[PDB]
View 1 (cartoon, rainbow over the protein chains, first blue to last red):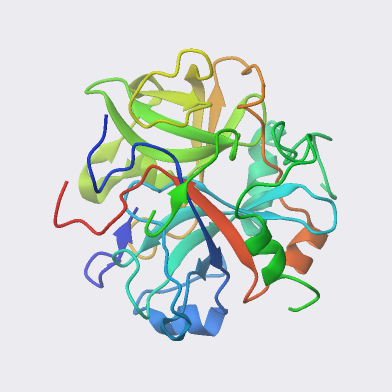
View 2 (spheres, rainbow over the protein chains, first blue to last red):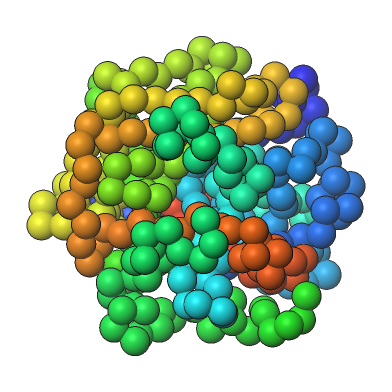
Length: 10
Length: 109
Length: 36
Length: 150
C-alpha cells in the first residue's frame, strides 16, 4: 500500500 | 484569472538529480530502477519541488554536447511538496524507452 | 536512437534556433562540467 | 511548482496540458515527443484508488499555452485523442512503478515557435547526463504550495 505509507500521486 | 496557490502562468524550477541510496533512504516506499528522485537536500538552502498538478509534466536536461533538450523524467509522485529530507519521484524515461518504441513502431520495436 | 531522432527535437524555435539563451539555463550548465 | 518562477513564452514548447471535456478541468501536464504522440503519467488516466478511469472521449490536449486560464487564441492548439496506451506493468497499488502512458493525437499537430517536440534520451546521453548533482528542469501549472487549501 503506497497510500498507507504516505505516497502522493501528483 | 487566478488566485494564489494556483499559478496564472507556467512555472519553472531547476532541480538536482539526487543519488539513489539517498532517495531510497528518504522513503518507506519501495523505490525501483524505473524512477529517480531530484530536489535540494536540507543542507543546501535552495528549495523547489513539483507539486500537486505537475503530474505528467517533463523533467528535461540540456546536453552540453549537442545543445538539445532531452526528456529524462516525468513528474510521478512525492510526499507533500518541498519538505526537508524528502524528494520528488519521476518516471525513468530512458529505462522505459523500449516500451515507448514498441508502441510507436506499431507494437514492434 | 543515438543523439537526435527528429533532427529538430529539443531545439527551441525561440532559443537555440535564434542563438538566444533563457534566463535560468546558465544554472544547469553550471551544475555540469565533467563534474560527475 | 514550489519556489519556481514564471517561464518566458516559448520556453518549453513541448509542454502539453491535459484537460477534461466535462466537467471542464485541468488534469495534468504532459509532453509532445512528436507531431502526433504525447507522453504523460499513467496515473493521470488510470488510478482505481480514486475511482479514476479516463477514456479517449473524456479528454483534450492543449498545446502551446502559457496562461492556465484563458484560451490563447493566436498560439494554442487543441486536439483530441485517437488512442491511449498505458504500460501493461503499471503498478498503482504498491509504488506507482512504470507510471507512464502514451497519447496518440487524432491527427498530427502543426508545429511552430510555440509547439515543438523534446528529444528522448539515447544510451550515451543517458550515461553522460544522469549524474547525482547535475540539474534538470521542471515546468507546470501545478500548485505553488502544499494543500490545506484549494
